[PDB]
Image: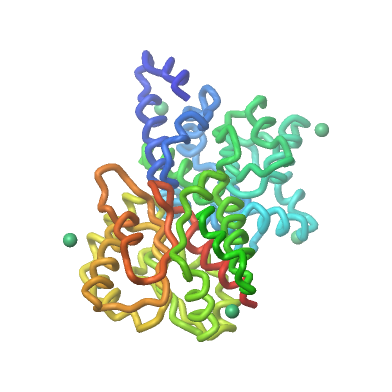
Length: 194
Length: 194
Ligand SMILES: [Cl-]
Ligand SMILES: [Cl-]
Ligand SMILES: [Cl-]
Ligand SMILES: [Cl-]
Ligand SMILES: [Cl-]
Ligand SMILES: [Cl-]
């Protein structure tokens, strides 16, 4: 986070973009704690911008997250938005984990994530875990993974495993997650490019 | 708060309901801090359950909050759900406050809130301030106010002024807010009644 201010000698404005992202998160959720907790892989920002400019696919885990995307701006870039499951009313880590336990083939829908797309997981730790495993096995190659699910007690070490991965990622070290946080972050990346 | 356990010698089960509500909030947003911050007026629970059983109106501030309500369960109870503005993409304290600045007439729509309804504010502090003022002037009489918007720096003392109000309320002492928290609280009150 604050270490990421090695971004300062850069020509790039990845400094300013990172702060916009933190600012939007705080303006969404209401606590400054996120500044410590938010971890962005080096070249996360850069990977995002290159993917979006290219008009990549976006894949969210639940519909709440997709519905919070700046759908208009994204479509102007040519990005499609899809979700792993279509259950309307997911509003909780539990509701999410149960929704994904009752769906038989969402793992297949995840495997098909096209090369170099953005994967944004806001609710379910199991999805994030599976996405990590798939990435390590080199079955999916997304351009970026925003993993911000809720973190419960004696959970999948999902966010902890995400941080240690080859693929650019944005995540929240710790339990905090859910809400619209993943959509909020991706939105911040799409405003700073339009 | 923790004090709300004067509810224990009660026959009532408002104890268990209060804990379920906190459990749901924590499961939604991901931090336990909320248990301190969450404040329920005495008989908030009781007033909510009476209104919901009666098939009251539910009025949220933005569409995100309504869309996160347990729409079916609420509909079986006879509750209609409406919103003060119909702008699709509100996702941030800033986005909420400005959306409410471009609408001329949400003030009238709030004044018309029917007697004994539930008022649920998840995003805009200015709406919450207005509703307090209207309640004090005795121009609206809702059954309950879930005020859980974000609290920014140099803000209206919106959630601060709610605590000072005659009408039963559930609120978050502090800045934390937004997300789906207001919907999640009302949902907890609707499950415990079905
Ligand atoms: Cl660039
Ligand atoms: Cl399925
Ligand atoms: Cl393993
Ligand atoms: Cl009762
Ligand atoms: Cl209007
Ligand atoms: Cl005043």
